[PDB]
Length: 49
Length: 49
Length: 221
Image (spheres, rainbow over the protein chains, first blue to last red):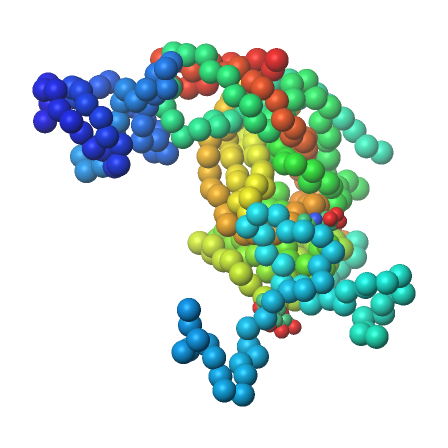
């Protein structure tokens, strides 16, 4: 579900927020992305990739 | 507990432990050496006396 | 089995790798880890010329090899490279890759052929994973895990390139010495086999991640 405030669990990581499509590109040894405050700002979907 | 599988009436002697090492192991380390351990200062020539 | 003046150079800004598996963008990030200090004195071995001595492995190793015909094959790591201790052997046999932790009886002048003369015996195996260039490598050994990082570049250079995770191995052994594996030609002839060796120690670095998530510069504090 996109563009709606949801509770989510991604591979065990829980949280709350809005999910959108990104322009980033992860190297194959990466699943999560952090910001300056160590908070999770990006995630790879384990089915669609 | 496994006293119903790994126990034998006359005594099971197929499970071994290491005594008499020179120094202490490091985490997740494995030593499978079979060498004669020198307790005193006599120079063991690969025999047990 | 067949029984057949040092040099130095400077490592400017080499031996940097990704410490985490996390993606970061347009930031400066500081981290403490085992790194190769900047502007360090680095040992150089050429290839008559045939340098394959036993070198120390203190707390990790940086390795570089500038070849053009693939004569540096792999390595052997251990403590006492005889049948009394366990030892690790990484080798490319020209068609496959082998790692094969075992109890090896190693020869004094091990080498390959343009043919396989490395060891005399192998008794107890605990692991098997049989499966104009620069080719930098980094080796570490922490808590029973042998870590490898690697990077490839066409064209010691004086730039910046960060090494990427390659593999971790659960081998569980004490490692104190290592030795390089070379292949000699056809009595024998050598070739271009310059290889460079360094040593790591704990340092706090400041790395710079660009907008695509790539490390482009670093500072040694």
